[PDB]
Length: 16
Length: 10
Length: 182
Image (cartoon, rainbow over all chains, first blue to last red; front, side):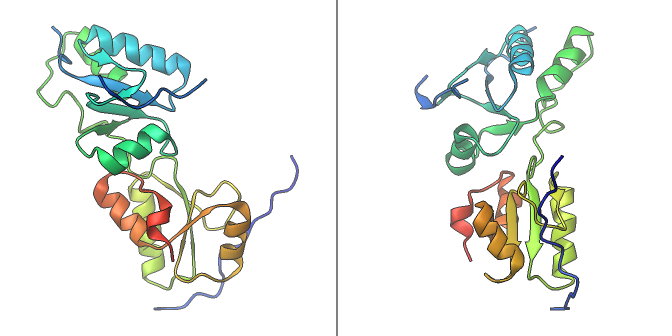
């Protein structure tokens, strides 16, 4: 019911 | 047999 | 006639209704059913990895098969219908998926290794989590920094290196996180 806290997936991704 | 881990308590 | 003679079955994190079905059917099949995890247990039917019984089998008893809750009802159904069984007794078809009940999130891992990890989590029965939420069970981290890492520490979520995943897959069991710290 109440909002949940989410840490978003990293948008800026890098190639190893 | 010898008890290694007991049953989970309800 | 007693296909499970010599089997010793134990449950972990199985609800009462399903546990009663499993013990009744396993006993009719000829197995012993143990409420405690005794030394002679051969098969552990598990509904979660975060239990003392599961942890003991994963750490100390690789001979013990970790089975899905559907194993005994499916084998019992074939047997009571008069179907031919084989010596495998459907065990290999009903092993518990290695990452059953795992909810795995990643942080600070580059491509293509990031998406390969995601694929292996799904292949081994886990849930993949792009975002970190309080119900994640494991955060695989490339480095000990960043927003997901800080929130996992706050929510007391396991933070492990990717070797946790590789060793859990080869051991066919979720391994404990303290052995895979960054």
